[PDB]
Every structure is written in structure tokens, then in C-alpha cells.
Length: 27
Image (tube, rainbow, N blue to C red; front, top):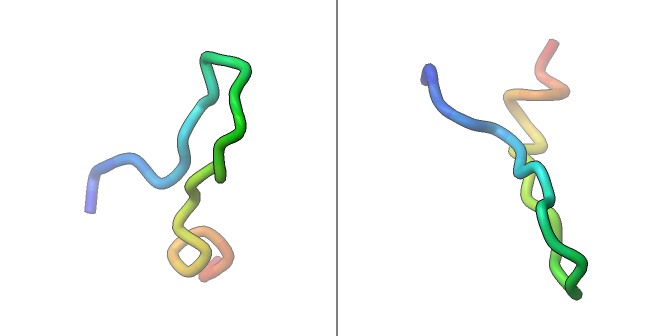
């Protein structure tokens, strides 16, 4: 992996916020 897994939001807009459900809760 070594990559991102979630997105830090920088603006105020209608946006589904991405996170990789697996790898995260996989611990």
C-alpha cells in the first residue's frame, strides 16, 4: 500500500467523503 486511505476535507461542499472501509477496519 503506502498510500492514502481517507480524504481530509478542505472545502465546504456536498461531497461523499472517501475512506477505504476494509484496510481501515481490517485492524
